[PDB]
Amino acid sequence: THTVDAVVIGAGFGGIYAVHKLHHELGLTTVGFDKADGPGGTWYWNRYPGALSDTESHLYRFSFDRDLLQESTWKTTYITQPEILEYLEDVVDRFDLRRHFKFGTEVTSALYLDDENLWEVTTDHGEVYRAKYVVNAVGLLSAINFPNLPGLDTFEGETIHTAAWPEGKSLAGRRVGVIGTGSTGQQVITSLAPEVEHLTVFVRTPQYSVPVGNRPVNPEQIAEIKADYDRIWERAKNSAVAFGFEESTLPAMSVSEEERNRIFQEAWDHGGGFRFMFGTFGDIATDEAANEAAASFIRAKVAEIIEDPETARKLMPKGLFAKRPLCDSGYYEVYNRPNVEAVAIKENPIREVTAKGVVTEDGVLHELDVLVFATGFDAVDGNYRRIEIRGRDGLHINDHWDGQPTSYLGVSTANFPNWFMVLGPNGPFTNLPPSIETQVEWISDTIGYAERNGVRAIEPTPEAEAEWTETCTEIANATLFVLFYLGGLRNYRAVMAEVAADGYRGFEVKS
Ligand SMILES: Cc1cc2nc3c(=O)[nH]c(=O)nc-3n(C[C@H](O)[C@H](O)[C@H](O)COP(=O)(O)OP(=O)(O)OC[C@H]3O[C@@H](n4cnc5c(N)ncnc54)[C@H](O)[C@@H]3O)c2cc1C
Ligand SMILES: NC(=O)c1ccc[n+]([C@@H]2O[C@H](COP(=O)([O-])OP(=O)(O)OC[C@H]3O[C@@H](n4cnc5c(N)ncnc54)[C@H](OP(=O)(O)O)[C@@H]3O)[C@@H](O)[C@H]2O)c1
Image (cartoon, rainbow, N blue to C red; front, side, top):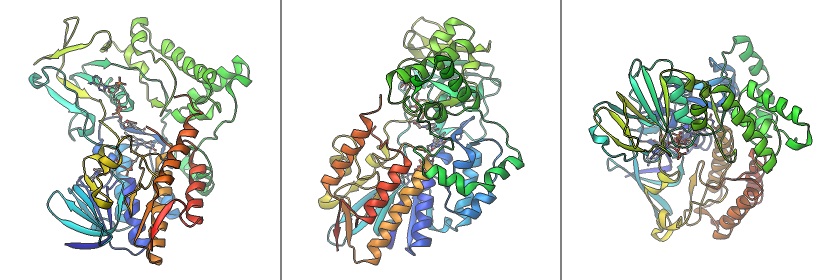
């Protein structure tokens, strides 16, 4: 029914910028879609208390508009969900993007029509769009992982998942249980502890966590940032992780024990997860001894913060210090509160939930009014895998990604022509907005090139896609241990630009 140049799926950072680029810069008629009733993406969905960025406020945003960077403000060194949502809502209205989005609208299929070199895209309300290009900015919020504890139906109190937090809902003065201690669960717990009648935490795997050091800013302090913003973004885009600190090249074991502690202590006092992992020493992710030095420093902090050694034993992180580091606003301190109990479910599993609360295998009823699930989601490619997406010859995305999801360059995959991914598989591990910008700017250039020239279809070769996996795999082999590209933002940007400069190396082009 509707003939458009381009379709964008999602209205988070990625979809917002994709619609801007395609509409404003390339002059294409572009429609965006989100199941959400408004823009924001993950910042629209996740409204739990204590929801906070792990990227400093001044860097958790777009950098493409130099005037916008002068204009935005923020209250603290890290940024909260309502502030981010407001920022993204403001971007949408600043660039008049709203009239291009269809909200409350799920894309249920995207089928390639081989004969016409078009994508046929349908919504859950039956609307059909024919488009030359599809840009998928669908994020990771797939189906909500909402675990199957026996007797859950019987609970007479409120059951809440953090990705569907009730707007009014304050749990002040209530008896609350939280299941899950990832970034989200830690954040909810710290938020809840001081206001809740009682808090019971069901801990399965304690994680490494460092202080975030979220502090109020002055208007003079924002003024300093803003006067140097160009240099700041120049540095970020020339770094590996783009978080606003100088990345260390210092081997942890090349200095004395006393200096190593001082270095760790400084980062601990300053705050920041990536700063702790990458700002202290150059080999925490690559050297077993370096990782142990970091890991055991955090363990010692846990033991020092938590008074009761039985409580401390349950919360004690173990093993390698890896993946996205967690940071917190006083998470370990919380367990020193008289009205907070930790339950280590590996050794004392949940037997059932009843009307009144949770019974553990010890046979003790933990009486609760409220049960919070901070249990995350199931999958990461989940959002691709639940849409009927069909490429060339009717090849389904699930048949194509028979094993793990793959991409060429993080943005495209073979047999799916003119179909792009923002933050697809095998892409950078990074402060995300500047990587998102990198990918959308590259997607847009590639679509510009296709439109300028005669291009009917562009897709990666199977061999390019395989060499990219091999490339990612060889970077990942160096590290300690989903497959990301781990060469960093600066390296990723050079790779993307060179692919473009080399006449789209690794793409099959139908002229
Ligand atoms: C609490 C929290 C804090 C975070 N902090 C940071 C941080 O500090 N730094 C950082 O770099 N990253 C952080 N992240 C990661 C974050 O996801 C990214 O920074 C960024 O918001 C991702 O934007 P996105 O557009 O790629 O995806 P999303 O924001 O996830 O948006 C995708 C949208 O696509 C929509 N969608 C999916 N499928 C369909 C469909 N079939 N039809 C219609 N719509 C669909 C969804 O409804 C969703 O709104 C954080 C995440 C969380 C949850
Ligand atoms: N960039 C950011 O600052 C940021 C912030 C928040 C979230 N995120 C991302 O968003 C995703 C969601 O984060 P999240 O913290 O909500 O989820 P998460 O990281 O997957 O954490 C889930 C927690 O729930 C526990 N759990 C899962 N199933 C359980 C069950 N059946 N019974 C008991 N416990 C169970 C897990 O323990 P186990 O460890 O044993 O599985 C874990 O503690 C993550 O992938 C994360 O990377 C990013």
